Image (cartoon, rainbow, N blue to C red):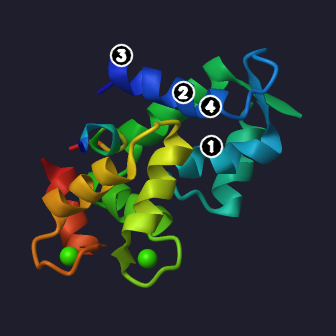
Amino acid sequence: DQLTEEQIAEFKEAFSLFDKDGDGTITTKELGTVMRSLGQNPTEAELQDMINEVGTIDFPEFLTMMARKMKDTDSEEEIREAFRVFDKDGNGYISAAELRHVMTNLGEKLTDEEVDEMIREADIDGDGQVNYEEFVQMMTA
Amino acid sequence: AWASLKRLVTR
Ligand SMILES: [Ca+2]
Ligand SMILES: [Ca+2]
């Protein structure tokens, strides 16, 4: 429906990682990076459309973009797109290394053991990595 | 452990 307080906090934390002087803006060239850190997988066309619909993007504009993407993208597609971003090398599995980088790029400071525990919770077939359906199982709850 | 990733999508 709309973004929760905890989603807003998480989006602000990711945005702020590219707002180096704290002035509430990122550059238009940084928008894609911030979106990908949040599990969005925008095409070049999608990014340029969002940029044109508003050389900087301020946080209220960004948050409005994110609220619309969250509400209007099909839920199954949202999961597919997030898996595609997080699976950095596209081999069909999120490795522990890839997942550590995802959590770091959100702005979190998880230990390596905490990320291993994320993997173990999701890993149903025991291969130590997270495939697409294992991700769906986590992300549908 | 997965709450921050789950928040990235809707159900
Ligand atoms: Ca991979
Ligand atoms: Ca697995």
x then y, percent, for residue A76: 27, 59
Where in the figure is residue A36, as x and y percent of width and height?
56, 52
Q: Which residue is mark 3?
A: A5
Cα distance between the residues tagged 1 and 4: 6 Å
Q: Which residue is mark 2?
A: A13
Are the residues flagged by discs 2 and 4 in contact, CB closer than 8 Å?
yes
Q: For residue A34, which numbered disc appears in the image? A: 1
| Residue beneath the point at 16% across and 52% down | A140
Tag 3 near tag 2, CB within 8 Å: no
**Distance (Cα) linking label 3 and label 2:** 12 Å
**The CB of the residue at mark 1 lies under 8 Å from ligand 1:** no
Tell me which label, 1 or 2, sits earlier in the chain: 2
Q: Secondary structure at mark 4?
A: helix
| Ligand 2 image-quadrant field | bottom left
| Residue type marked 2 | Glu
- x 58%, y 57%: residue: A42
Say which amino acid is labelled 4.
Phe
Q: Is residue A25 left or right of residue A78?
A: right
Q: Residues within 10 Å of mark 2 (few under 14, many from 20)?
A: some
Sequence-first tag of 1 and 4: 4
Mark-to-mark CA distance, 4 and 3 = 15 Å
Give me the chain letter of mark 4.
A
> Which chain does the residue under circle 3 lie in?
A
Q: Earlier in the sequence, mark 1 or mark 3?
A: 3
Nearer the observer, disc 3 or disc 2? Answer: 2
- Quadrant containing the N terminus of chain A is top left
